[PDB]
Length: 162
Image (cartoon, rainbow, N blue to C red; front, side, top):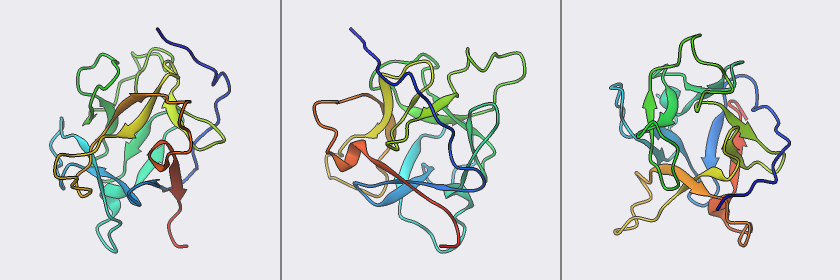
């Protein structure tokens, strides 16, 4: 029912960086300037200013923390499932092993972002009924190796001050 071929994992770019979904050309942002925890993560166009919420950093623990929220990407259910929504939650303490943490993500050289514990689950987006690109939420989607030529399955990383 599941398979993984991404035994290799690389680290995410150091410093501040933007995770841009190539399909929409938008970068991960909280739902809508929500500093409240439990807010879903959605895609938004790059902002000339106040893009701190669009800035993410890779902590040594292996988690990505939002610069503005200071919160880390996490599962809404808290249980990793296919199609599970991703919401921002408080960072885990030191009482959680990094290998038992779901906030740990792995990055392949291809630029695909998957879970370090569930390589079959990767970050993806789903179309909306009104196809509103401004607000497309990210959710865990199983790898679609059948179609890796999709821009939706491709993520681009951008660094500040190009």
